[PDB]
Length: 296
Length: 293
Image (cartoon, rainbow over all chains, first blue to last red; front, side, top):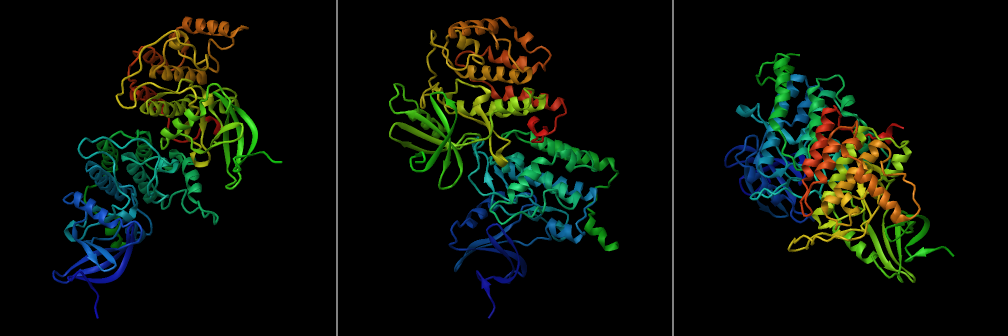
């Protein structure tokens, strides 16, 4: 027979995986809406999915935040049902043969910095900023970048008093070593500035095709991240951003300078890229590389 | 047979002397890792080790604080094993022909000011700030400045009431006289302002290569101190910092004006240098002087 979670959610193909497990394609039969079901094995060891849902619900209403359909349990699984979105930026990147033009990077950067700014206004740091955790909407929302996966996210200040978490060393879960900030590598607690730094890397990855510390291929020993850490701290911003508009190097440097508790000047950051956008004479249409690909 | 402390670490070369003990090289036989061993003879008239191990423990979790591995009582000694770290800022200074470039000095100044700030948030004052008490980490943490040696550390306010300690004078000089603040030389009770003033002299030591009171000939130690104090008190900060970015002069001045119980504004003090780092067009890379050799 057919497999249906909840009652209304027809389970489907395994379309991917996230932090708390796998992401399956599903269908709300009682509504005919294709949705995304994420299910974590009831008792793994650290049942973090009931936590992620909480965050999504705190962010509910924000621009570019996926809507949650249902949260609950079904046997050996606790399922979260959320809005199915378009391809991730990684998919689109590969789709474009791993080549984003400056305009698209600038067009994207503007929205990515806004999603990041929003999570922070709600007292949280994302902690795992990568091209996979951003998706494009569908249909009418086709030009809006969405931010997903609040698995490694953390509250960085009291939601009432707004008192920032203290400066100490990390005793938590880390994200992708490839887009990690230098502090993450130094073993320091992550905060607002670190989310923006990784973005600097995501942006440079989109411009470069791949990062310099990417694919070092180390030995069988436990830490390959030691090489990444090194390659990363040894590669100066001026060399990394070589051959590109200074706004990118100026972006990374600024983020590196910020103190653990400084509130970032987001507008300044949006300002750098917009000025460059207007300079190169770009129209602010939401026509991206992947839209032009249909004509060659 | 082989010298084995607590049946866990083999003892090695004495690599120095802490505030009240000797630091020996050690090897966690099991994990093979290199550690640092501090020893205090049980028959000491002024046991501090049990006090110091406690302080390191309170400090645990802070950025740049060394880890204590084990504490044990051997036959004739009390033992405190802690993680071994990299070279100190003195060993690197000397390695670098005793010359630190502006950005290396600024990049360190920021971390050094963070550590002191941290300790103060824990209700303690270091009271012996010098380059020897600052060590770089190992491997990936090799870009992190650590603070060590809490042997002379004193609590400056109640752990609960936060009632700052009383003003007292006629005290004795505590710490290296070369970096000791003018107040320390005047036998005045130490507080937060003193830890930061001394850090000031440490920065200029890195800039200048030597300090105006360093090298005075004297036989008697109190005579030594008397001379050092004289030169120090008689050397204008404006003159001292001659030719270096005013920020340093601004720093020492600020420090020498905080009232005894004043809560230093560590952000302003850091903002000076971060602003200077910025005006010099310095970029944020973790490559230091010693890395260009």
